[PDB]
Image 1 (cartoon, one colour):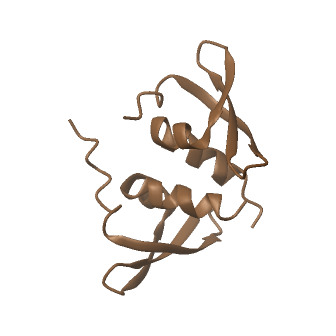
Image 2 (cartoon, chains in turn red, green; image 1 turned 180 degrees about the horizontal axis):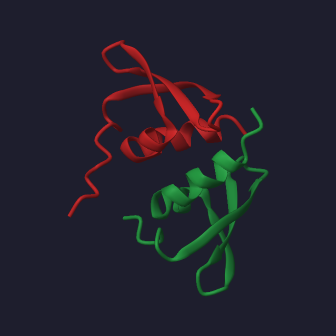
Length: 61
Length: 59
């Protein structure tokens, strides 16, 4: 049933920077369409807005 | 539409064509190998693509 889990594609404005943490995880810093800014684990952003993440990686190759 | 997520084993390499497009080389769970434009793999198997980019991160 669930695959409509990618609900952040239309809420995010852009992916800004990425950083690696001590536990070896990646932290994603992004900006929302309302102007707000925040950071989240890549294991979350990959599932909520995968196409936004892919565009970021290609312009950074 | 990602009907390839469960059929693809891994993404192996990528090449930036002359016209600027990206060509993706991959391996299927049945052992075969093939290449396809990134516009196809991005929508058919996005999670496999993201795994490749994360392992290809040197900052």
